[PDB]
Image (cartoon, rainbow, N blue to C red; front, side):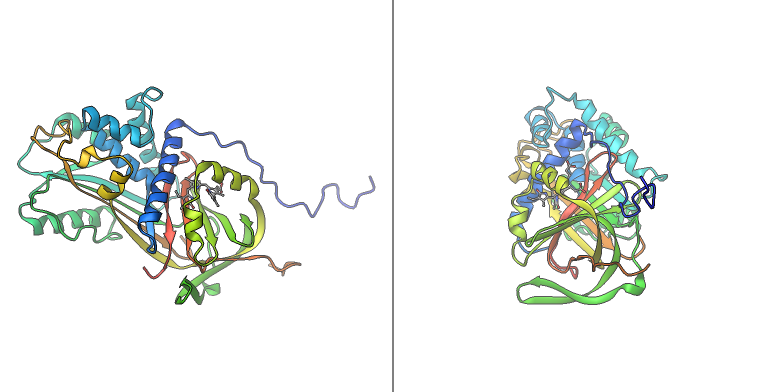
Length: 381
Ligand SMILES: C=CC1=C(C)/C(=C/c2[nH]c(/C=C3N=C(/C=C4\NC(=O)C(C)=C4C=C)C(C)=C\3CCC(=O)O)c(CCC(=O)O)c2C)NC1=O
């Protein structure tokens, strides 16, 4: 052992970690995210998609607190929960914990979230629903007058503006004068890179919207070690944020993204997780500020959640109005990419440039819940 060094000086950093342990609520929310995104990707073929699956699941679980009978059990089941395995109050506790761990400010996270139910002023909301909506979901039930449509538009939008600190200024264009309950759910996420980008290295480049459409956007560029994988047909990278959150990105050749989106599930995700390795790469990301607005009635109905939006909804846990139903259900999510949320290598590293339509997934590493997923089809909205 006449070795020049007592340890191999070329060996890269060790990156082993313990096995990801999952709680059953997180697994249900993860599988619901896949189911919902695949359908959304079918129904909106060309646009940007930005949704928070855990926040949609949370809003419906809150709605189930005010539901009874088949209306209640259908929501719980279609969210992926089996009440023969999980007591119902552990579901509400799990969504409560997710709010607390994200709102923990010793955690460095720029994740603003909000959920509110706007109801008719002339009807009294049950106190037990008011109590649990505030306790478990930090959600307000706000009286409104929908017969005067224009004040509700300004009021709902101003509420969203206030709770997002002006980041989401508009969520509702108009509301029917016969509305009973309006579910309003919104998310803003700014990527707070664990390793920020240098603004000096940001350059304008081509983003290819489709086989014949190209737009000019600023591209951030950084050289570093990232967990990655690539073939001739796909590249994928995991980018850590601060505060125990990681963003996964995947990109295919032009026009093949749909083939990827319609094949996503957890089992295939875990297989790719084992293939990916930490490698030195050049990473190019478009500067970006993209929005997605979701009509939750049409989307959730295709997923089997129908009663709560129907003329036979049993929402007597909220109010004793005869035919109370959720008339409007909106989910708006915003995501922003900016810069701040050395000798030459022997070989030029592979350049992971995301200048083609790509999909993204933001995951809370403490809970494993999907905080945000979607598709960047055009970083210019
Ligand atoms: C068929 C190919 C296929 C690929 C390439 C794939 C990749 C993939 N998905 C993952 C996780 C994940 N992927 C998602 C979800 C999504 N992923 C998205 O990019 C989008 C838009 C969604 C939409 C719902 C979720 C929820 C996880 C976490 C799964 C878990 O931790 O159990 C990971 C792990 C990332 C990491 O550990 O750092 C990879 C590699 N998934 C697949 O099924």
